[PDB]
Structure formats: structure tokens, C-alpha cells
Length: 87
Ligand SMILES: [Ca+2]
Ligand SMILES: [Ca+2]
Ligand SMILES: [Ca+2]
Image (cartoon, rainbow, N blue to C red):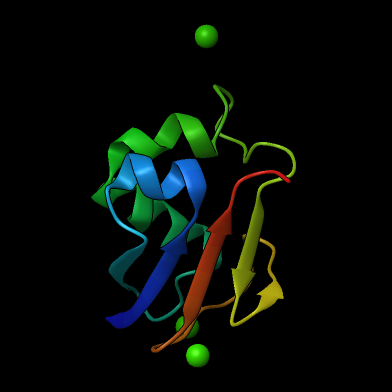
């Protein structure tokens, strides 16, 4: 599908064991779908990203190509996605 890459920081990078993670998602995959692909690649991330209700924790900052992105936004091949824990 569409290949793209996540950058992870601080404890998220530590849990994943890498500062970068490649993912490959569907053509109409959202940012949220790309985030679920990241967590599928490194399931230990799950409880550092989502609460028991499945919702993103408050204050996590998801970027797509350097701009804040909501989980329903589109993705595209070559995207640079970033996941920062709360400031
Ligand atoms: Ca797309
Ligand atoms: Ca519980
Ligand atoms: Ca770039």
C-alpha cells in the first residue's frame, strides 16, 4: 500500500526500541489507521498511546508532515508522521 514512516520520541521510542518505524497502509488509511499500524508493529506502545476506552490520551501530539493532525485526516505515500508524548 502506501509506505510511510513514524518518528517516536522519549519513552515512546524507548518502548518501540527505535526512533523510526516504517509502516505500509491502505490507500485511504487515515492517520489513526497509520497509528494503529505502528502499534501493531510494536504492541507494547498501546498503553502509552490509548486509554482503556481506546481513545488517544490527552496531550499526545500527532504530526503529519510537520503539522498537527487529527486521527481522521488522510495519509499518503512518503508521509513523515511523528508521535510525541505530552509536553
Ligand atoms: Ca491516502
Ligand atoms: Ca481497566
Ligand atoms: Ca522531510
